Image (cartoon, grey):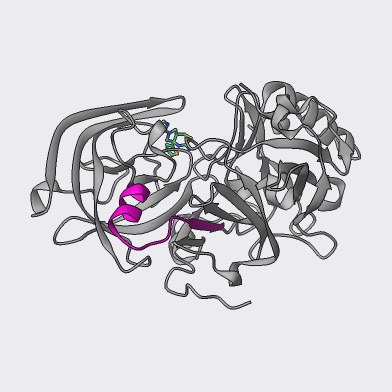
């Protein structure tokens, strides 16, 4: 396997809890900012005024190429909000395609619980489609601008690399967190074959899950439950989030598989860390989890399989110790399945917008042990898969 995108390999930093970010520049002369990669939204928005958690921000008055769109944007969401002022400017990705484009930028002037202290990022790059752009679908997303203005192919791919142990702010800064390959697929980043699932509709990166197993045991729910009210691939969410009913069934099964050790309710609620003596995390007592995805061929599916090394998220201990500690990174949702960063860390994920499909292959940087690895396997004969989609 040759790796043909060396300029873009290792261009990300960060971690599942705080997000993965890429360096970008905005304006003339270029202003460097670190930008969260978010496949779950569609706005390019950057800090544009002082904030306690920002060491730098976009200064529109210092950019000769700034254009004011004379329009505000207000983006409240469950956990937080940002608001700002729309404009356009020249934008580049230094460890990216060697192109500069004119793109929409939301200059964030006010926010609440958006910026994260010590995350090292100063804005967000929404890579999903115009339908979910704010204030409306007339605000062309960055990637749409990039493809229209250049010869960059209509595809990007993400290798998010979890360390398997905690990183502090300085360690994030010095460590490679993965790769965002703009316009292609780098074969060095994965092992085995790429398997593709259709993008059901171009808004979020929406997919259809057709079967779920815990250690090979079918969760045995009607497959519509798995996609109620949608299933998406979202680098801007930390956890694997499952619809309430599915979460309840999955947690019951995971508890049963891991029952040789009892964990407190707060662990299963994703709130409380668990710790083990250094090196002794009992990976083998925890089950693998397989999600079967609709394939491209009629009546065919494939599965992706993750380990506890994916769904147990490393965290630092609440007190000074050499223990290995984790939070359970599967949680309930009222807005559908979210395949967040902890599941993406298992895989190289190809966002093939041109062919309306998402590819999965085992990541060359997934965390595993000597006994088990993540997997992408197929095909399986699966009937009536369209019925798994929620309307
Ligand atoms: N993937 C996610 N991205 C957001 C993130 C905010 C901060 C980090 S990830 C931005 N967001 C959003 N929603 C609607 C329109 C625009 N953005 C929701 C929020 C949590 S989940």
Front one among 334 and 368: 334
Residue span colored magenta: 142-159
In what quadrant of the picture does the N terminus appear?
bottom right
Up the image or down, 333 lies above or below 292; here it is: above
Give the percent coordinates (x, y) of residue 361. Answer: 67, 59
Q: Quadrant of residue 51?
A: top left
Q: Quadrant of residue 246?
A: top right
Give the percent coordinates (x, y) of residue 63. Answer: 11, 53
Please name the residue shown 87% across and 35% down the image.
218
Front one among 288 and 320: 288
In this orientation, does residue 121 appear?
A: no
Up the image or down, 321 lies above or below 51; here it is: below
Give the percent coordinates (x, y) of residue 140. Answer: 30, 41
Up the image or down, 27 lies above or below 385; here it is: below
Up the image or down, 341 lies above or below 82; here it is: below
Q: Quadrant of residue 377?
A: bottom right
Give the percent coordinates (x, y) of residue 334. Answer: 60, 21
Q: Is residue 103 left or right of residue 223?
A: left
Q: Is residue 96 left or right of residue 59?
A: right
Please name the residue shown 48% across and 44% down the image.
39
Please name the residue shown 34% across and 43% down the image.
141
Q: Please give the count of numbered marks on the rendered protein.
A: 0
In the image, farthest residue toward the right:
260
Is 71 in the magenta?
Answer: no
Where does ligand 1 appear, by image quarter? top left
In what quadrant of the picture does the C terminus appear?
top right
Front one among 89 and 342: 89
In the image, farthest residue toward the bottom:
2
In this orientation, does residue 380 appear?
A: yes
Front one among 199 and 21: 199
């Amino acid at each position: 396997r040759r790796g043909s995108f060396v300029e873009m390999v290792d261009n990300l930093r960060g971690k599942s809890g705080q997000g993965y970010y890429v360096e970008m520049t905005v304006g003339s002369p270029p202003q460097t900012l670190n930008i969260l990669v978010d496949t779950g939204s569609s706005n390019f928005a950057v800090g544009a005024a002082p904030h306690p958690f920002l060491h730098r921000y976009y200064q529109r008055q210092l950019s000769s190429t700034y254009r004011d769109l004379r329009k505000g944007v207000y983006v409240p969401y469950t956990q937080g909000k940002w608001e700002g002022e729309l404009g356009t400017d020249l934008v580049s990705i230094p460890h990216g395609p060697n192109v500069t484009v004119r793109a929409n930028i939301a200059a964030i002037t006010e926010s609440d619980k958006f910026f994260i202290n010590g995350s090292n990022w100063e804005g967000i790059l929404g890579l999903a489609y115009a339908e979910i752009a704010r204030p409306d679908d007339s605000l062309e997303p960055f990637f749409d601008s990039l493809v229209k203005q250049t010869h960059v192919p209509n595809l990007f791919s993400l290798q998010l690399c979890g360390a398997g142990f905690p990183l502090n702010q300085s360690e994030v800064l010095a460590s490679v967190g993965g790769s965002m390959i703009i316009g292609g697929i780098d074969h060095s980043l994965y092992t085995g074959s790429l398997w593709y699932t259709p993008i059901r509709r171009e808004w979020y990166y929406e997919v259809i899950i057709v079967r779920v197993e815990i250690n090979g045991q079918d969760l045995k729910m009607d497959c519509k439950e798995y996609n109620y009210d949608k299933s998406i691939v979202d680098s801007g969410t930390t956890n694997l989030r499952l619809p309430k009913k599915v979460f309840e069934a999955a947690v019951k099964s995971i508890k049963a598989a891991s029952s040789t050790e009892k964990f407190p309710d707060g662990f299963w609620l994703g709130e409380q860390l668990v710790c083990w003596q250094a090196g002794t995390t009992p990976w083998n007592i925890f089950p693998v989890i397989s999600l079967y995805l609709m394939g491209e061929v009629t009546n065919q599916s494939f599965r992706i399989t993750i380990l506890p090394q994916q769904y147990l998220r490393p965290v630092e201990d609440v007190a000074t110790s050499q223990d290995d500690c984790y939070k359970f990174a599967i949680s309930q949702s009222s807005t559908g399945t979210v395949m967040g960063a902890v599941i993406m860390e298992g895989f190289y994920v190809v966002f093939d917008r041109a062919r309306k499909r998402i590819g999965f292959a085992v990541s060359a940087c997934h965390v595993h042990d000597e006994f088990r690895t993540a997997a992408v396997e197929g095909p399986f004969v699966t009937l009536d898969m369209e019925d798994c989609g929620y309307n």
